[PDB]
Amino acid sequence: TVDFIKKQIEEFNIGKRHLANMMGEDPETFTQEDIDRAIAYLFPSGLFEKRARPIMKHPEEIFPKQRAIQWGEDGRPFHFLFYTGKQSYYSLMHDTYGKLLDVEKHHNPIGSR
Amino acid sequence: ANHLKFIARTVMVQEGNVEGAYRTLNRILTMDGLIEDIKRRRYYEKPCRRRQRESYETCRRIYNMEMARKINFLMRKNRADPWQGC
Ligand SMILES: [Mg+2]
Ligand SMILES: [Mg+2]
């Protein structure tokens, strides 16, 4: 799916230029703020749900993140916790617990949630 | 009826609180099984229907004894756990 991200980001920039030149702005200082105004004026959909309105955005905000390749071309997996089926979770867990242990050997309402 | 009166099943209220002394006597009879016997003996209960009672009671007593023991044995490990979030 990564080839899709390369391609999409390329075409996104080419279409970005294409947008600026017709909309008649400097392609350099063009922002998302300007992207919105632009499409909103070109394809004016009265629609209540705002996700179903036209979008041109950087594919990263469009597409979901992906889980990277989890094993080498030998079949052998990179992370040692892979077989847990959640490596992402238990890595945080291993690290957290490690932090704790080290703290125990060493040691001898701001609106924050 | 041939025995001297007032020696049996008698509490004497202390510091004039009656309700307390009655609770006390009640605890006596119920500790010895006399209340369950009065209540048992209001009507009859036939011999078979009695061994059934006996056996159900005694099974149930065995179960509750064992389960009690097991609970009070595992009691220690109720203590807040050391290894959390390993
Ligand atoms: Mg008489
Ligand atoms: Mg009995």
Image (cartoon, coloured by chain):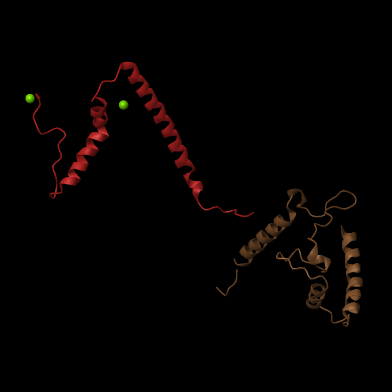
Chain colours: A brown, B red
Left or right: A21, with A58 as reference point: right
Rendered image quadrant of residue B41: top left
Q: Image quadrant of residue A34?
A: bottom right
Indicate the quadrant where residue A106 lies.
bottom right
**Residue at x 67%, y 61% (from the top left corner):** A96
Residue A97 point in image, percent of width and height: 66, 59
- A21 left or right of A104? right
Residue that appears at 25% across and 27% down: B37
Q: Position of residue A110 (x, y in %)?
A: 57, 75
Q: In which quarter of the image is the N terminus of chain B?
A: top left
Q: In this view, does A82 lie above or below B49?
A: below
User: Which residue: 34% across, 16% down?
Assistant: B48
Figure quadrant of the C terminus of chain B: bottom right
Image position, residue A2 (x, y; %)? 87, 60
Ligand 1 positioned in quadrant: top left
- Disc tally is 0
